[PDB]
Image 1 (spheres, rainbow, N blue to C red):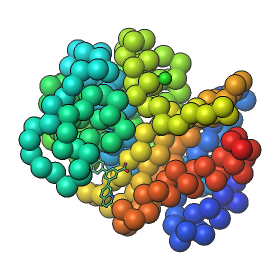
Image 2 (cartoon, rainbow, N blue to C red; image 1 turned 135 degrees about the horizontal axis):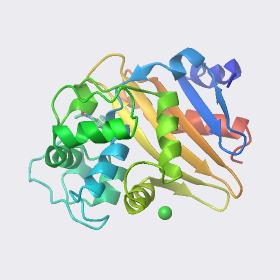
Image 3 (spheres, protein in one colour; image 1 turned 60 degrees about the vertical axis):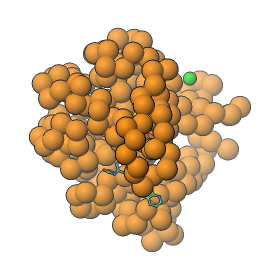
Image 4 (tube, rainbow, N blue to C red; image 1 turned 90 degrees about the vertical axis):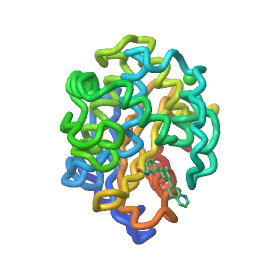
Length: 241
Ligand SMILES: CC(=O)Nc1cccc(-c2cc(C(=O)O)cc(-c3ccc4cccnc4c3)c2)c1
Ligand SMILES: [Cl-]
């Protein structure tokens, strides 16, 4: 591991504070601007949709990435939530109510067992089964996110290969002739400190770079900084053009 406080400039310039953690898979080396915060545990918020999707798929709660989850007809304040969704769009638009139904059908017992099998965070689902990742007891650090993401990438999690391929498909965020990004955003507001997440990885021709970042997010106005700051670090380290 190596600490590179020069990255702190990317947060300071936006009057923000946070951590970026990078892992070079070929060289098995990690890099971060803040070793302490890289190991501080936060609510996973919507980044939990990764493990939740894996479990729902492996148990048959979700048949496949085409199954339609019909809008329940309750108008919510995020327009894209008031519509039918499948796994792909539910991930893309971080559709909480779809994933809350997943968790209810999963149930406490199976959720707890699977999170321990995943070695996911503190593996603590204390709270309500349909909201614990937003205001319950579960916590995960940036370094712990990378550990989990690396297992998913290599199909080494204790679910089927199919379940892992589908979730990695649903994580697809950006792709061009230079790189592919599979990732999931998060926004934790119910428990202080309010933070934004972005965790995932960058696929190159002959390497993969895992990343996990969180940053202080007092207002939703700064949510775009999650990706922007992360990409500035990637550019600085010459991982992307
Ligand atoms: C119910 C609960 O626990 N909330 C929660 C749970 C899971 C995900 C999110 C969430 C994620 C994102 C994201 O990942 O980008 C963005 C927003 C969000 C929220 C408010 C906004 C206001 C103006 C403009 N844009 C906004 C955007 C919310 C919130
Ligand atoms: Cl894909």
